[PDB]
Image: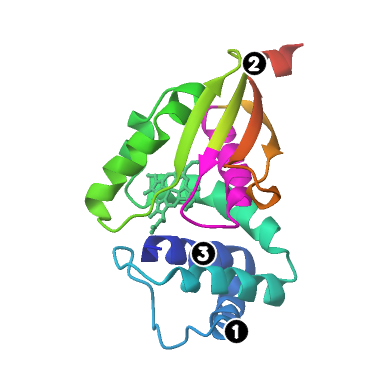
């Protein structure tokens, strides 16, 4: 994946766990030779997956737990490393934003020309509810989507309940996420 993902992982770990840890994790993963990650440089996917497994071990947290946290972090990280304007243009509400994710990764592709973006399809079951279809060229990153949606909840000041209703490793087409999202009414009543 692009070095931007790998720096984001480095920055997330260096923030919550201090720099000694991150360089322990970097060693377990087998990546000392890489003196640092370049955002715009494509890397073998190995680099990302190996960091996650190294992080899981050194930190004693499951891959799934780290992915869920990363997914939330990425929302923040992207808006602060100079992609705030893409995020902003993609929508002014969760439902709007969800429908333009492919369009967003299309726009990202201009800056990152070897991107292998994910694919999202939105089925609006109401103005409080949606089915999210996630399709990926890769395995094992459905948990990141949990995290992302939690970040997007905060983004739109919306409370988002997410249960994954379909799982690819049970032989389904794509991961499906059933999504319940409510604003001010959660608070006042
Ligand atoms: C400005 C905002 C964003 C940027 C710059 C961005 C960029 C990227 C990049 C560079 C990758 C790595 C893929 C590769 O190198 O081939 C990626 C992966 C991914 N992005 Fe985005 N992204 C953005 C927003 C989002 C948002 C809002 C979501 C919300 C759901 C999302 C979901 C994902 C997922 C799930 C992956 C994992 C790859 C896969 O499924 O195969 N991204 N993105």
Q: At which x and y percent is residue 159?
A: 66, 27
Find numbered disc 1 in the image and state the secondary structure of the residue it sits on: helix
Q: Would you say residue 46 sits in the magenta stretch?
A: no
Task: Judge from the rendering whether residue 123 lies leftward or rightward of residue 43; answer left or right.
Answer: right
- Residue 68, horizontal then vertical, whole percent: 64, 51
The one of 152 and 62 positioned closer to us in this rendering = 62
> What residue is at 56 percent from the left and 80 percent from the top?
29
Give yes or no for contact between labels 3 and 2 (Cβ–Cβ under 8 Å).
no
Query: Residue most toward the front?
Result: 171
Question: Which of the image's four quarters has the C terminus?
Answer: top right
Kindly state the secondary structure of the residue where label 3 is placed: helix
Ligand 1 lies under 8 Å from the Cβ of mark 3 = no
Residue pointed to by mark 1: 28
Q: Main secondary structure of the magenta part?
A: helix
Label 2 SS: helix
Can you say whether 95 is above or below 163 in the image? above
In this rendering, the answer to whether 79 lies above or below 165 is: below
The residues tagged by marks 2 and 1 sit, at their Cα atoms, a distance apart of 46 Å
- Furthest residue in direction bottom, as rendered: 33
Q: Which residue is mark 2?
A: 184
Dividing the picture into quadrants, the one containing residue 67 is bottom right
Q: Which residue is located at x 44 percent, y 41 percent?
A: 119
For mark 2, does the 10 Å Cα neighbourhood hold few (<14), some (14 to 19), or many (20 or more) residues?
few
Circle 3 is placed at which residue position?
9
The label number, if any, that marks residue 67 in the structure image: none
Which of the two discs, 3 and 2, labels the residue nearer the N terminus? 3
Q: Position of residue 164 (x, y in %)?
A: 69, 38
Q: Which stretch did the figure color magenta?
A: 134-156
* Label 1, residues with CA under 10 Å away: few <14, some 14-19, many ≥20: some
Image depth: mark 1 or mark 3 in front: 1
């Amino acid at each position: 994946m692009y070095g931007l993902v790998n720096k984001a992982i480095q920055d997330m770990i260096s923030k919550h766990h201090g720099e000694d840890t991150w360089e322990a994790i970097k060693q377990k993963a087998g990546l000392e030779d890489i003196d640092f990650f370049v955002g715009m440089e494509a890397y073998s996917d190995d680099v990302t997956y190996h960091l996650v497994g190294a992080a899981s071990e050194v930190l004693g947290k499951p891959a799934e737990e780290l992915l869920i946290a990363f997914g939330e972090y990425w929302v923040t990280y992207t808006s602060e490393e100079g992609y705030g304007e893409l995020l902003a243009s993609a929508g002014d509400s969760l439902p709007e934003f969800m429908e333009n994710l492919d369009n967003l990764h299309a726009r990202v592709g201009l800056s990152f020309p070897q991107l292998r973006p994910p694919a999202f399809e939105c089925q609006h079951t109401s103005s409080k509810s949606m089915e999210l279809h996630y399709q990926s060229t890769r395995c094992g990153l459905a948990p990141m989507v949990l995290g992302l949606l939690h970040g997007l909840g905060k983004r739109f000041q919306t409370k988002v309940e997410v249960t994954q209703t379909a799982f690819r490793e049970t032989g389904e087409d794509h991961d499906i996420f059933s999504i319940k999202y409510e604003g001010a009414e959660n608070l006042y009543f």
